[PDB]
Amino acid sequence: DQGAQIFEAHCAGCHLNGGNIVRRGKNLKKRAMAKNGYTSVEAIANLVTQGKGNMSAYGDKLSSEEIQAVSQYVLQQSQTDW
Ligand code: HEC
Ligand SMILES: [Cl-]
Ligand SMILES: [Cl-]
Ligand SMILES: [Cl-]
Ligand SMILES: [Cl-]
Ligand code: NA
Ligand code: NA
Ligand code: NA
Ligand code: NA
């Protein structure tokens, strides 16, 4: 799975198993993702592309296709509770 591979290589440092070791209240599990509206590929992809706060932008680091793939992976994992 490309999305999983991208996640392992670029996201798992902070978000292993859907957590967030940096910002406790902003993890990738169902509750926080739903509360914050990260419930579509597009919502997730927008964040990954642009960054926010202490999370880097990935729009000049990952391709559009890679961003879509990792965003779909995160969506599916979050909706099903990692
Ligand atoms: C640590 C250096 C991080 C890496 C690597 C990635 N993310 Fe991240 N993410 C981080 C922080 C500090 C935050 C909070 C941003 C804020 O201030 O609100 C986030 C948030 C997310 C979210 C939203 C989670 C939520 O609101 O509950 C998503 C969907 C997310 N991060 C995805 C994501 C992906 C796919 C990454 C790899 C490309 C990635 N993050 C890397 C910190 C860090
Ligand atoms: Cl794939
Ligand atoms: Cl990768
Ligand atoms: Cl933070
Ligand atoms: Cl950045
Ligand atoms: Na890997
Ligand atoms: Na913290
Ligand atoms: Na670049
Ligand atoms: Na940069």
Image: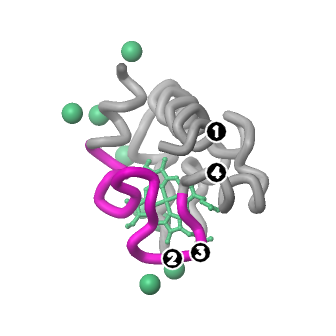
Cβ of mark 2 under 8 Å from ligand 7: the answer is yes
Q: Position of residue 68 (x, y in %)?
A: 56, 29
Residue at numbered disc 1 = 79
Circle 4 — which element?
helix
Q: Position of residue 64 (x, y in %)?
A: 53, 31
Q: CA distance from mark 2 to mark 1?
A: 19 Å
Residue under the point 59% across and 68% down: 26
Q: Position of residue 62 (x, y in %)?
A: 42, 39
Residue 17, magenta (yes or no): yes
Amino acid residing under circle 1: Gln
Q: CA distance from mark 3 to mark 1?
A: 17 Å
- 59 or 79, nearer to the observer: 79
Residue segment shown in magenta: 9-27
Circle 1 — which element?
helix
Amino acid residing under circle 3: Gly
**Residues at marks 1 and 4 touching, judged by CB atoms closer than 8 Å:** yes
Residue at numbered disc 3 = 25
Residue at numbered disc 4 = 30
Q: Earlier in the sequence, mark 3 or mark 1?
A: 3
**Above-or-below relation of 77 to 1:** below
Residue at numbered disc 2 = 24
**Residues at marks 3 and 2 touching, judged by CB atoms closer than 8 Å:** yes
Amino acid residing under circle 4: Lys
**Count of all numbered marks drawn on residues in the image:** 4
Q: Position of residue 18 (x, y in %)?
A: 45, 53
Circle 3 — which element?
loop
Q: Earlier in the sequence, mark 4 or mark 2?
A: 2
Closer to the camera: disc 4 or disc 2?
Answer: 4
Cβ of mark 3 under 8 Å from ligand 1: the answer is yes
